[PDB]
Image: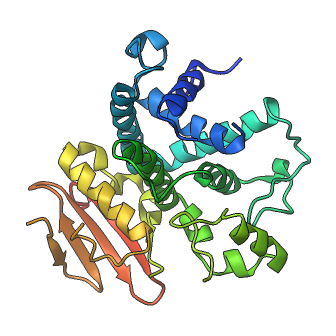
Amino acid sequence: PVTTYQPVEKQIAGDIIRVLEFKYGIAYRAKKVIIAYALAVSGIHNVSQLPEDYYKNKDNTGRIYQEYMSNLLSALLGENGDQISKDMANDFTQNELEFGGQRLKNTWDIPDLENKLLEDYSDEDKLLALYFFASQELPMEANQQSNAANFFKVIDFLLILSAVTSLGKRIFSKNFYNGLETKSLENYIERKKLSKPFFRPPQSNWRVSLQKLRDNPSRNTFMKMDDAAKRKYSSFIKEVQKGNDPRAAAASGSNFEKLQGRDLYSIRLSQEHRVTFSINNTDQIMEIQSVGTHYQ
């Protein structure tokens, strides 16, 4: 929604990032934005709403952090996830302009954006900027239990964001990379700035399309489901956006059905709720038709 010098939610996010030992530049501030919003949607707007030892207790804070991140994942998967993602991306971009050394007539070193002044940034450009910077310094190949799970919550967020918004269509197409200068691509791959699963630079390619729910939010009734149906849908979107085939229903655990229609399928999430989708086999796109109670 909104966040309340720097906002208290970002100061708290800074304490959380430190005590969970993520590692203080723009990749850190991008993650600070994300965790600030996870706090916001969880109703944390004062330090007095946290345990007094939140800044010093890795084990306790890791637990509440993961709860907060899951609340944010649900918000992204809900009716308003697209605008929420754009709000967060704009929050990030605005704060690099006012509290950072960046001008309106200035560029960032981002793939598919190196020649674009910041004033001309569309909402999707801001999504790409938040995505790109947040993804850096972030271990997909983590090490220790509980630690790893903390870093993985940021993976989930970014991937879902790419699925809930139009961003995943941009970054997971081939023209995103072959449309760059070869020198640009070179330093991007060499400095590991295009790590997987965040990017798919040359050397499967499935992705999720939630366009039908952006154009018609009444098709998304994700919020009416129980937590277990929500977590199954979250995992389903996550797996396909990592590039795996839509038969990721295998994350009685699998309920893959085929409905009446050209390549129209469904997965039961609960006895009342389901997710409905089509499968474009040639373009490697799974298009969500509804989530929640069934559309009429």
Residue ranking furthest to the bottom: 282
Give the residue drawn at x 78%, y 29%. 99
Q: Which residue corresponds to the image point at 13% horizontal and 65% vertical from the top-left?
A: 253
Query: Looking at this view, is 225 or 73 the one in front?
Result: 73
Residue 275 image position (x, y, % from top left): 25, 63
Residue 267 versus residue 20 in the image, above or below: below
Residue 208 x/y as whole percent: 43, 69
Left/right of residue 1 with respect to residue 217 in the rendered view: right
Depicted 269 relative to depicted 6: above or below: below
**Looking at this view, is 289 or 30 the one in front?**
30
Of 107 and 21, the residue lying toward us: 21
**Place of residue 226 in the rendered image (x, y in percent of width and height, measured from the top left):** 19, 44
Looking at the image, the residue that sits furthest to the front is: 144
Q: How many marks?
A: 0
Q: Residue at x 56, y 70 (%)?
A: 169
| Residue furthest to the right | 105
The picture quadrant where one finds residue 92 is top right
Q: Position of residue 37 (x, y in %)?
A: 51, 33
**Horizontal side, residue 5 vs residue 34: left or right:** right
Color encoding of the figure:
rainbow
